[PDB]
Amino acid sequence: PPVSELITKAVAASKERSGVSLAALKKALAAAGYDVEKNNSRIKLGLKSLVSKGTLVQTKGTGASGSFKLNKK
DNA sequence: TGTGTTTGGGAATCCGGTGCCGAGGCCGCTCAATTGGTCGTAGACAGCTCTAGCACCGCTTAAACGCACGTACGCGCTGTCCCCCGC
Image 1: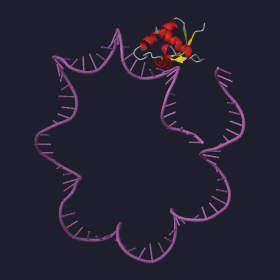
Image 2: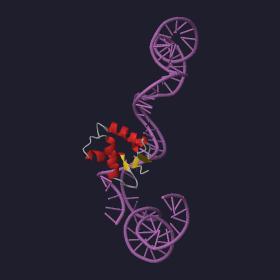
Image 3: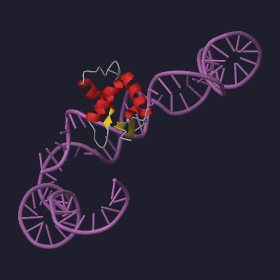
Image 4: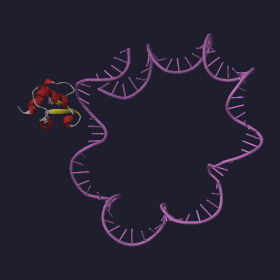
């Protein structure tokens, strides 16, 4: 399954008012059996694609270093 | 949601009493500083030599300088996780 679903599912499972950090996303995908080490660069890209698709709102920071929430709009 | 002011309350500080022990003074003594004198020599001074430090010049080339260009490291920001702190 593509990493955009795994990320969206992790952000939905940890839904809050702040927003899953990249470190929490790493932890959730690793707990989901996804190798976050080798494919970290893929994650940053896929995450960026999800922000560029507007599917994730950046709530703090800039780019992948930030916190993110599912764009309910 | 955010900026700003206020109060009980522990903790450091001030003040007065007090008492106690070491610092300051006094005395008797002694031994080390002082006086005077002799004598030896350490070094102050003159004087002489020669070396090695300074100033200069010219030439070559290697290093320093300025500049272009790119990337990688420093630094700021965010997050988390845990391990020292206060009690």
